[PDB]
């Protein structure tokens, strides 16, 4: 019996598994329960702490994936399938995973906590691209990742009601962070050095923990990759959440909040999932049905409001974006777009595309978008129209909300580092026109290129090692920089400096799409208020 | 008596004068009466045709400048005083000038008609920079220029009333054009080949003659230099013209506000000219630059609808137009009110001065509209750089008032039947007295078009004399053929169209073809901003 793979936590005893990497072994504890199964009467409710167990919990394999929609846009295509559930779906899904060096650290080790981010409707800690073994081995941190409820199960809200208060998937995350505070020391982790990192909806999640005081005491540093809590997709108003929840009930044969939720509770999980997309108010891309709601509780105000009012002295943040944030989303509803052609669209498609990529705004607001994103010397060139609509969706949804967050945080006391990730993976299965799409820096951060059975280049492995070092440096010291030899400067509202991350050495540049983001962040809100 | 200097027009006999020019003699008939003097009871009224006369009228020197405000911003400074009256002020000013080759052409010769344009408030055909002798000598055309009423005397309007119907200054221009039709043949001119050209308010005037059917039959081609009838300064609505007229009257004691229109106008008619002028600038709704108190009014008469509407509804087949701007349309205007600006320093302004200047340069729009201007003209990587801010405010004023109105006109005309040629004038005269930061300001292509550098008493470089000859050739070629191109191996000037949007750079180097008249900027002013003002 291997003693390194036996751990006792507050709830009881666990048995882990030894994992191999090209650099040596790692200890892994997978499928550790942190909450009571949120089933039956517990669907839509805040998570309850896992009651203590007797015996030894088998923690050698990933647990079930939280019930969610399965992407069938391109059946059998790696580009979409790598994000789909790779374990059975279940509402009994509140488990987390701990990876630690082998043998276990005998002294307090810095902790990284990963939050996955498929638009709050999808994701799992078990996805191959989130394999913690390489980061933990190379950088000697403790890595934790958790499953949290998504879609209706995590975010359906009838605001004010006790039966479906909203944001429960976020509370799942907070519970797991509490679990980390109380139990990570048993693995060698240092609960006084916990860095949150997340991508997309996971990045929005991290930002939300920053702005919610009960969570703020559970970690120390934050990394937000291609996502921000002030994103136009990341929250929904009380009224619109109530309407979406109400339409879901109607669509599945249910009728008073109590009676409505009770009837929803009798429905099979899959039935809810089958009608998830139908509650959106219009055809769109980069919009999701069930997301965090501003209700006065978890978020006492809108993320924008909470951001502007915040004192962020003592906070270090790492934020950044990929080179082509918008491209991926275009194939899910923008007219003329497909991974299977050049997607060289026409002006008319571009214009219809703008209403899809910027849904629910006035005709005037749309016209303003078209003004800023048209090259009036080349108003009808298909290649430029393709690039421009990608820019619209990417700026509006990701780049500009991240830039706004970064600027406010920097100006209000936080030390901020910003990056643009510009490397297109040699193994990327998406077409060349998509460039470096959303989500495709993650495999480098997790050091997936070090996996021998995969086809990455020697250069790419070295690059992955650089990135793991930046991320782990940040977790350890709040500063990604290595000892001097080209330096990564902090981002500030004025100088707006960030670095490019690719195969070349760090290059320092200015402005996260400053011209475009002035529009989304300064002008467009004024317009919409009148 | 010299037979070349004697001419009989419908109204009676004329005696002219023989002018020396560096390249030979020209006949000039200066100060020909074309209307009865708009004096006393005729103030604010449409012009009456000049009654025939017995004997010989001496047309041998320029007549009076129409009563107007005199620029006192920089007393003594050549850059401003070159535009100031160089004859006595008088309401007796309805005189035109004709220059013809010596000896008088044997066969009918194409005619250029010049219209000056100091914002509808100033200007005169007598200005040194409008001397027609050099054009006529170089290119053997006939040149005509006229004085027309400016300021209140030309454009004060109480819409609806017979006593001050508005647009009488434009009626002055039209009467002169009618005169050209009836009389220019007597000077050897061809009434079937008349090309109008004007700069600033003159350009806008030319545009209005294009959009007003009774004027449209009096000419065949048009040249609009740094102005357009659709500019935000060039017309005013009926209600705003009434408000301005009424406040002027009120400021000078009429009546002893509003009331009977006939009575209010009768009271205004008893006021000395200079009294009206002293209060001209006071009727503007806010502090501004590039805004003028009394301008053409959309009356439903001379202009049946807004120039924008008329341009859009127009069929312009069989029309040739030459349009253009200088390199720095906005700079001249900034020293007349934009905080931080002066000809006497670098005008390196602060961000706060920039924001304030935006409201001066784009007066009377919503805060939201102003915010939109700030958005498009701020460089968000250098939002506070003084030099960039100075240039940005210049571009705001130039784009909003000149470049974008001209581009909109040019695009609509081309798409609706007209052959259009477009230019940007990029030479800064060696003799320019304005500071270097102003670049090539509004109005500074004129001296080259008229061939002023050929004047021996002036100190232009030899290159500039070559340049002037080139421009005079383009202008006259256009007058003659409707096409500025030489009727060889010289680079060609292509038509401007809505799609390719091609134009030429006019400077000391040969023609260079380019695309887009500030296209990104002008999409904001011409396509977006109006949608914002509605909603
Ligand atoms: C590129 O493809 C899009 C998407 O269409 C799908 O993918 C293609 C590879 C092919 O399998 C199509 O038949 C698929 O429907 C094309 O946009 C569609 O065009 C069809 C007509 O062929 C039209 O009925 C649909 O409405 C369009 N779908 C969308 C997403 O708008 C597009 O024409 C292709 N562009 C090219 C040819 O460059
Ligand atoms: C540049 O000049 C402007 C205009 O001021 C005038 O011109 C100067 C050359 C100098 O001769 C001044 O005395 C003139 O009054 C300056 O702006 C003015 O600043 C003063 C107070 O300092 C103020 O009373 C005026 O209202 C201002 N005028 C305007 C139109 O803003 C400006 O400060 C000068 N820039 C410099 C020196 O950097
Ligand atoms: C590019 C693929 C993506 C990214 C964003 C979203 C919103 C959905 C997605 N399929 C997905 C699904 C699950 C997940 O964990 N991350 C992501 C990231
Ligand atoms: C650059 C100087 C100008 C230009 C525009 C205006 C409006 C006034 C001005 N002083 C002026 C005055 C009289 C005139 O005939 N033209 C002009 C052109
Ligand atoms: C205005 O006053 C005059 C002066 O007597 C008068 O003749 C005229 O009819 C009046 N017009 C109107 C419309 O009141």
Image: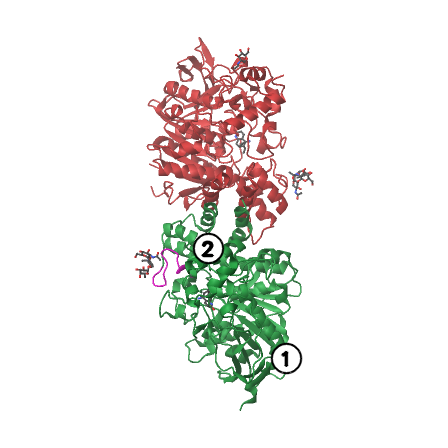
Chain colours: A green, B red
Comparing labels 2 and 1, the label whose residue is closer to the camera:
1
As displayed, is residue B535 above or below residue B101? below
Mark 2, secondary structure of its residue: helix
Instruction: Give the magenta range.
Output: A329-342
Residue A39 or B418: which is nearer the viewer?
A: A39
- Badge 1 is on which residue? A108
Check contact, mark 2 vs mark 1: CB within 8 A: no
Q: Residues within 10 Å of mark 2 (few under 14, many from 20)?
A: many
Q: Position of residue B309 (x, y in %)?
A: 42, 33
Residue A334 part of the magenta-drawn span = yes
Which residue is more in the foreground, A142 or A33? A33
Visible residue check, residue A401: yes
Q: Chain of mark 1?
A: A
Q: Which residue is mark 2?
A: A392
> Which of the 4 image quarters holds residue B264?
top right
- Whether residue A182 appears in magenta in the rendering, the answer is no
């Amino acid at each position: 019996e291997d003693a390194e793979l036996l751990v006792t936590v507050r709830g009881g005893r666990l048995r882990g598994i030894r994992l191999k990497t090209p650099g040596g072994p790692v200890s892994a504890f997978l499928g550790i329960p942190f909450a009571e199964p949120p089933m039956g009467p517990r669907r839509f409710l805040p998570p309850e702490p896992k009651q203590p167990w007797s015996g030894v919990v088998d923690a050698t394999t990933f647990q079930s994936v939280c019930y969610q929609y399965v992407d069938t846009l391109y059946p059998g295509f790696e580009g979409t399938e790598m994000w789909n559930p790779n374990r059975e779906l279940s509402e009994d899904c509140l488990y987390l995973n701990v990876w630690t060096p082998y043998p276990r650290p005998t002294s307090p080790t810095p902790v990284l906590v990963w939050i996955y981010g498929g638009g709050f409707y999808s994701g799992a800690s078990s996805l191959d691209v989130y394999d913690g073994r390489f980061l933990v081995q190379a950088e000697r941190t403790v890595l934790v990742s958790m499953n949290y409820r998504v879609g209706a199960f995590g975010f359906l809200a009838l605001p004010g009601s006790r039966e479906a208060p909203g944001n429960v998937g976020l509370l799942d995350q907070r519970l797991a962070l509490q679990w980390v505070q109380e139990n990570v020391a048993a693995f060698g982790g240092d609960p006084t050095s916990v860095t949150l990192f997340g991508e997309s909806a996971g990045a929005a999640s991290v930002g939300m923990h920053l702005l919610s005081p009960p969570s703020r005491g559970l970690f120390h540093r934050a990394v937000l990759q291609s996502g921000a809590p002030n994103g136009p997709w990341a929250t929904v108003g009380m009224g619109e959440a109530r309407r979406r929840a109400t339409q879901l009930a109607h669509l599945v044969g249910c009728p008073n909040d109590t009676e409505l939720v009770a009837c929803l509770r009798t429905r099979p999980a899959q039935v809810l999932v089958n009608h998830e997309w139908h509650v959106l108010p219009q055809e769109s891309v980069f919009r999701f049905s069930f997301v965090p709601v501003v209700d006065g509780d978890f978020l006492s105000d809108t993320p924008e409001a909470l951001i502007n009012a915040g004192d962020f002295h003592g906070l270090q943040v790492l934020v950044g974006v990929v080179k082509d944030e918008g491209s991926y989303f275009l194939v899910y509803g923008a007219p003329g777009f497909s991974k299977d052609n050049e997607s060289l669209i026409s002006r008319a498609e571009f214009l219809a595309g703008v209403r899809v990529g910027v849904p629910q705004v006035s005709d005037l607001a749309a016209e303003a978008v078209v003004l800023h994103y048209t090259d009036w010397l080349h108003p009808e060139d298909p290649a430029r129209l393709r690039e421009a609509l990608s820019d619209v969706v990417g700026d509006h949804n990701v780049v500009c909300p991240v830039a706004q967050l970064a600027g406010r945080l920097a100006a209000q006391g936080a030390r901020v580092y910003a990056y643009v990730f510009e490397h297109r993976a040699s193994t990327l299965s998406w077409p060349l026109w998509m460039g470096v799409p959303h989500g495709y820096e993650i495999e480098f951060i997790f050091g997936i290129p070090l996996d021998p059975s995969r086809n990455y280049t020697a250069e790419e492995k070295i690059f992955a090692q650089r990135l793991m070092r930046y991320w782990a440096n940040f977790a350890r010291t709040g500063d990604p920089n290595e000892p001097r030899d080209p330096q990564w400067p902090p981002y500030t509202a004025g100088a707006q400096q960030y670095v490019s991350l690719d195969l070349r050495p760090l290059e320092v540049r200015r402005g996260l799409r400053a011209q475009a983001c002035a529009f989304w962040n300064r002008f467009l809100p004024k317009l919409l208020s009148a």
